[PDB]
Structure formats: C-alpha cells, structure tokens
Length: 284
Ligand SMILES: Cc1cc2nc3c(=O)[nH]c(=O)nc-3n(C[C@H](O)[C@H](O)[C@H](O)COP(=O)(O)OP(=O)(O)OC[C@H]3O[C@@H](n4cnc5c(N)ncnc54)[C@H](O)[C@@H]3O)c2cc1C
Image (cartoon, rainbow, N blue to C red; front, top):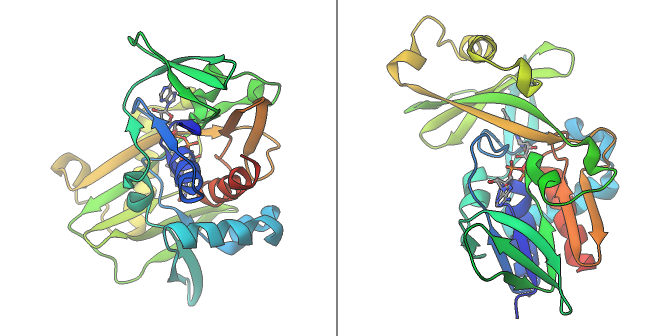
C-alpha cells in the first residue's frame, strides 16, 4: 500500500515527497531532526542569473513544479542603483507542509524484500514497508546508501541570521566579493533574513568564524554596534549543506532497483530539489 518512503524532511525530502504525493502516490516520510541540518538557514531565493549552469532545460520545469505545488513569488530586489527580479518559495511553507505523514524517528537500515524495501527504525521491532525508497538525508545520506558519487559527499557549513520584529523597506543584494553576495529580505511579515553566502569546511568552523559572517550581515542592514546577538534580537541559523563536486543540478541516482539517493544540493539548493522531484514523478 505505501508506494514510497522518503528519508529526510529537509527541502529535498519535503519537495520530493510532496511532488510524489501530488502525483497520486502513497508517500511516507521519516526524519530524526538532527542538529545542523542544511535546510533550517535557507531563504529559498532563486535569482535566474545564479543558476546559469543549470540550463532552461532544468530551471524551467523545476520552477513550474514549485509554482504548481507551493506557489512562487516574484520579488523586486534592490541591486545598487538598479533592481532585479528574484523568485521566492516560502521555506516555512515547504518545510511545514503536512500532506505527507512523517515519522519523527531515526532510520537505521535499508533492506531489499521480495515486494520492495523495508526501512528499519531505531528501537522498533518492525520495519516500515514501501515499494521504493528515496534517501534525501543531506550530508548524512552516505550513512545509509553508498556509491562512487556518494563517496564524495562532504559538508559545507554556513550561517544565516534572522532578526525579530523587523522588516526591510528595501530588500537587497550586495556583493562583498566575486560570487559572494550579502542578501537581506523579509522572510516572514515579521522577520528579516540576512546571509553572506559563505560556505565553510565544518572543521574550520567556530564562534570566531560565525562572528565574521554576523558582522557582514549586520553591517548590510545597519545593526552593527547594537549588540543584537547578546540582546536576543537576532537568531543565528547554522547548517551543513550536502556538497558533491561535479553534480548536475544535484545528485539523483537509483543506487539499487527502487532505492534512490537524493542529495548534493549545496550548489543549487531549492531549484535543484524541484528538478529532482520532477524527475522522480516521471521515473517512479
Ligand atoms: C547558511 C545557509 C544558507 C542557505 N541558503 C539557502 C538559500 O537561500 N536557498 C536555498 O534554496 N537553500 C539554501 N540553503 C540550503 C542548501 O540548499 C542545502 O544544500 C539544502 O538545505 C540541503 O537540503 P537537504 O534536504 O538535502 O538536507 P537537510 O536539510 O540537511 O535534510 C536532511 C534531513 O535528513 C534527516 N536524516 C538524516 N539521516 C537520517 C536518518 N538516518 N533517519 C532519519 N532522518 C535522517 C536529518 O534529520 C535532516 O532533517 C542554505 C543553507 C545554509 C547552511
């Protein structure tokens, strides 16, 4: 009766699971909410010039899927003296959607059965059953499935900041280095999100490194000097992105019959989740 089990309910598991559910499948999710997941700090802003490598071949079917399922909003961002249109999917809408039921437990094993796949859970005598399994477990995907591509999965950490009870009159993109932009916008009607775009080897991460990105972000919105961290006015959101070098969109591979690995979204984020989901609707 269960068609697909999706392991992981970050952006990639959430989007894939709901696209399959919308396509008529019986989908079940499993997620253990482990700390440092990649999707908590995400803004889900998609500027078309950021995704040139992808190609209209993939950008457009992906954006259409996200618009059909969640709705895509067009935001006119300030870019110096000029303006630029950026597409937005509300991350709270993607990550909080409840169509797909999610077991808030830890997957410990995957086993082929005669009818499909059995998904073991920590501390559970029975396994969850499905014809197919999509493992969208972020940087932890290689803990459950292995492949030459997954042998290259590493984490690229980063931080973004959310200021409470605040709105920007001007949502902006401002560069601080080639291909490094400080982005500030109204992520909710009450909150301002700012990120500087840096990615870090999770080893080279510490409070000093975080304060460097905080200084960038707070100067871009004129909050430097106000001690907003110590005062509780801003939340730091740390996450580890799943990076695999050389990935086309992201990694979507059928490692065994019915067993898919969906990860490697550090490079392109939400738009490549949309591409992968459209692929899975076609192929499952
Ligand atoms: C600072 C920062 C800024 C970002 N900004 C953006 C942005 O503007 N736009 C954008 O699109 N993206 C953004 N991202 C996100 C980026 O695209 C990530 O690559 C993306 O979130 C990856 O999502 P994922 O679903 O593959 O992984 P994750 O979000 O890490 O999800 C993996 C999930 O799998 C679960 N899991 C793992 N193993 C198991 C197990 N054994 N059993 C059960 N559950 C398990 C984990 O608990 C977790 O919830 C940002 C990330 C960071 C850190």
